[PDB]
Amino acid sequence: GAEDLEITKLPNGLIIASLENFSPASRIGVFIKAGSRYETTANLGTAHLLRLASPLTTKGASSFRITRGIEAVGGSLSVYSTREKMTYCVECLRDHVDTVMEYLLNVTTAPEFRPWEVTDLQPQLKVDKAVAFQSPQVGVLENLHAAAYKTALANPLYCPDYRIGKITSEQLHHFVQNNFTSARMALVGIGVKHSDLKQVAEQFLNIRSGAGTSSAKATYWGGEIREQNGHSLVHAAVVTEGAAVGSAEANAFSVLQHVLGAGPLIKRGSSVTSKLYQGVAKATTQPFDASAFNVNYSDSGLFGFYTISQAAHAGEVIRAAMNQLKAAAQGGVTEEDVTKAKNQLKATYLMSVETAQGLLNEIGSEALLSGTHTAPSVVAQKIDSVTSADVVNAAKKFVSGKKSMAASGDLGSTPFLDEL
Amino acid sequence: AEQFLNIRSGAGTSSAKATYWGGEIREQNGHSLVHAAVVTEGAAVGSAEANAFSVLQHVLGAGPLIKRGSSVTSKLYQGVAKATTQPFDASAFNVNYSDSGLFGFYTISQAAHAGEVIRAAMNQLKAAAQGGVTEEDVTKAKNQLKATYLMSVETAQGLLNEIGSEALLSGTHTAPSVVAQKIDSVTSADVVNAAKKFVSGKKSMAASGDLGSTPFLDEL
Amino acid sequence: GRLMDRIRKWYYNAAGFNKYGLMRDDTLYEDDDVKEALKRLPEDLYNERMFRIKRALDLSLKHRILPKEQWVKYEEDKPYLEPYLKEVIRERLEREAWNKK
Amino acid sequence: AATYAQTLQNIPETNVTTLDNGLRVASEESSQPTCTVGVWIGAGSRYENEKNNGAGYFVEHLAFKGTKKRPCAAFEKEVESMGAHFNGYTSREQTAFYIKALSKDMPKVVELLADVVQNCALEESQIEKERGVILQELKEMDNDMTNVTFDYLHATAFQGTALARTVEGTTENIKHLTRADLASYIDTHFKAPRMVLAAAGGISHKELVDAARQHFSGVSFTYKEDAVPILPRCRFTGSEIRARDDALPVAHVALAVEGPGWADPDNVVLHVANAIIGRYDRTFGGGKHLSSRLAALAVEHKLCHSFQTFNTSYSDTGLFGFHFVADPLSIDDMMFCAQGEWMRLCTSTTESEVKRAKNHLRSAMVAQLDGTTPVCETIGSHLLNYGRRISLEEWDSRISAVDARMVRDVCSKYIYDKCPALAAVGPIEQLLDYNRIRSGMYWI
């Protein structure tokens, strides 16, 4: 056992990916093009509430059976989502796939959003959002997207406060009817035979064809949102419009990322292979952190750096992170740096798929925003095929582009976007 | 004051200079009404350039004088009126601080119509910076200003405030005839210039409500 | 069959709650199921039930009833809760059955 | 397609070969381009004494700051530049250093590992720097109630013994430990017969062991050197420690009885038992419909922010209990229901409950082998604790033999009428009296 990865594409545009790795456990998932991106000032947060609504009664199964049912076979059911993609997946031992499938099917294609259930659920948005925001890390990213854009992506990933309790069963239904359409959905599935996963997608996935609501283009604003809140630590993120998914310039940034440094590889260790880290290190004396920030969205992307530092030293720390970006845009990139990075990137990519979750994600992401599976050797071929110039250019694009900044903490000594 | 006050001498902590940023803070909160304010570095207190703005203020229109009435003498109001159809409000915003000041307009309008309403308020500002100010408008204003000033002192509170404000940021009492002399002594040009300073200067904007149709500072 | 379909109309008038302007569902003893159902009623239905009931209590204390014109007519009686209540009970029976299994 | 039963059988076997110096080499070869290899050492704070407590942790901090063959800068640059991830940890009875890299580099990796455990530089200047760092990590960890509570749980449950100590050590030990003590610790504990080189991913057992013989040399002379030392047993004590700070927002409470220790089979039943009670946290969407009774009650009565059951094992002993986080005014009811559920375990478990508990347990064990690092962790641990690998196929066999009747007997055997160990931190005024708790240990 060890071979293939079939991938049909039914009549209505519903893509079905599949790979049998003979694992004792399966993991099926419904990827969908949907998220706070398609929200309008009128229905903000509805995507978030929908995320928390996965366990509510459906036309085929009740709130009670959904949970007891899945749990009876040691299974699990969860919903992960970004500003533009929502994944509903379930895990369980091979022998229970058929059982767990019923609920996955029901949740994504037959919700009832009964008013009362929905009313009792809403206060959960307050809770859910409260734990997430315990990481300053999350607050600035929300504000970043709100400063980097004027629409679509500018929309927060967590239901704004004023709207908690105001979302309606209508909005949920309408959001689902206009986005969870066969042409926007993919039924991926590790640990199963393609014929089986396909026979399912057919006789049962009802909500047929369509493309429904189309997200407005991602306009770029380039704003600066600051948040004075006292924290001894200041989190700052400065970016610029970057590459989009499957963009040619993408691979370039991803590499400039590792060159600048994106995450430590040695526990409690210093990062020498990180120009950005190393640069800041020579600038400040106290504890801190700095990384290359890089997001690639359907019709846009963000690139820059993210820094955490003691308040009084945010000034020196941010400047440093900048000088290190300019210094790179001016040919401050060795042919070797480009070599090292390329490896760290290939390695990171390859390790990030040992996880049942990691693999399903990789597979399904393609099968949704493509319909094909770029072989690993191909993705490799595409990565190293990035010149030392491409990298220096990416860096240039940053130093020149219009920047947007998001920071939070005791910003008393934190510089403004126009002072960098 | 003497034989009693004790914490004394010096001027202690000095405030840092007022640096100008020119940012744009938006607040999405759902309100059917959107409040927006667009300004630019205005004039300081005690500054000669003050009087000019104060007047451009009345010319553009700053507050109604007739209950439930329309403000014709308000170019800004009148301008916006021709632009939108639904209820709203618009005024000349003007603040004068020790080492700086702010000037512009403030607008309240239904969400969906904030776009048209703010544009209107703008066009009416540019239109004024391009000599769109009659020698009469300058005359009317000057009166509304002198009147407003004079009425704003009938109040025990209003009077003490006026008096005390000078005795603190000065140490003298500019006679009412003098403040009058200073006000009308403002050319029609001064006014058109003030307006220019706005259209050219770097603007900062603050809005809040269902900003779904509210424009960004860079779209004005 | 349309036999007791008459008997009902008879009983309905014998009962007499319609003289208080009450719907059949307004007269239900509020046990657990009924209590849950009531929490599910839309706002408007809920407030209408409330006024009807308060109105009846006031008549009851006064020892009066509504004028004959205002009595609810057998065929115009709204079974506004029966739908919710039927659901609440199935859910319960589902859980009960499942918890034995 | 293929059944769960079969997929379990077709799992590549774990190869183990012992060298001549006593070191054991094991691995599970997969078809993966990326791999994980590292050494799992049977050492930790339990092996420390009152004077070197924290050394093994201090050694964890230097383990990566360079060896003698290649100083700090070089070492890091060499690992970073090959896209390899270097990580590790140290607990009460087990330490580890492992690397995540491409199978291609497997041999160079093994050389790096062996260089780390055998040749730590222990630079005098570095030590003074990690000294301040560790002191900082102490103040940070001091604000993690969950760990402060488990430390206290050990501190009292195993009071007056080695297991009573924390892994990081004391403030004193850290302010004074010497280059010598750190050297001594390494030279005393990091030894072949007590280590295991485990690897998972796309790797040839043979290529592994070959690269092993090459870099793991140090062959012992005396019989003392290759004899694995038996630790003095740690006495358990039913008792409590209450650290009260009403200023803290929520309280943490942990209760536990003495567990059997790695070797014992009952641990399979205990884990099944823990699955019945399970866990919870305010973000479990299942809410009031969760199968776990304690979870349901927690939801229905807002009993706590979260709770977890655990069966922490050690060589000769362990801790079987639960920990919850609740608001000052719900501690009492939470504890009440919790102990209540334990009594249900001993007296009235249902086949339905165990049936479900088993499935949850199966998924859990499978989920513990989701990746190379986790498979490697399992191998290193199993060898060091069971002296061999236990395949999921075996685990499943054992797990499937458990039934209601068995859960009740095992639980009664470890829980019923036992004096527990209690640790409570925070605004705990409403939780109270050991006596009252002790009574919650009997009569369903």
Image (tube, coloured by chain):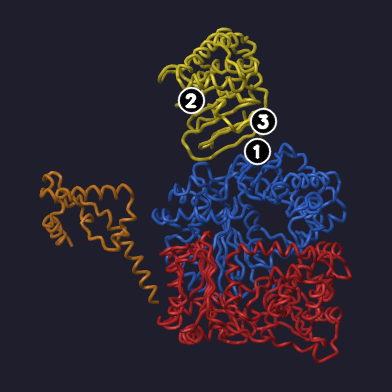
Chain colours: A blue, B yellow, C orange, D red
Q: Which mark is residue B18?
A: 3
Where in the figure is residue D401, as x and y percent of width and height?
53, 86
Q: Secondary structure at mark 1?
A: loop
Residue D220, quarter of picture: bottom right
Give the amino acid type for the residue marked by disc 3 in the picture.
Ala
Q: Is residue B101 above or below residue D263?
A: above
Task: Report the chain holding disc 3.
Answer: B
| SS at mark 3 in the image | loop
Q: Is residue D106 left or right of residue B12?
A: right
Give the Cα separation between the discs numbered 3 and 2: 30 Å
**Numbered circle sitting on residue B89:** 2
Give a yes or no on whether discs 3 and 2 share a subunit.
yes
Sequence-first disc among 3 and 2: 3
Q: What type is the residue that disc 2 sits on? A: Asp
Residue D150, visible in the rendered structure: yes
Q: Note whether A43 is above or below B131 in the view shown.
A: below
In space, the residues marked 1 and 3 are separated at their CA atoms by: 27 Å
Marks 2, 1 in one chain: no
Q: Please provide percent x and percent y for residue B103.
A: 60, 24
Mark 2: which secondary structure?
strand
Q: Against A350, is D239 above or below?
A: below
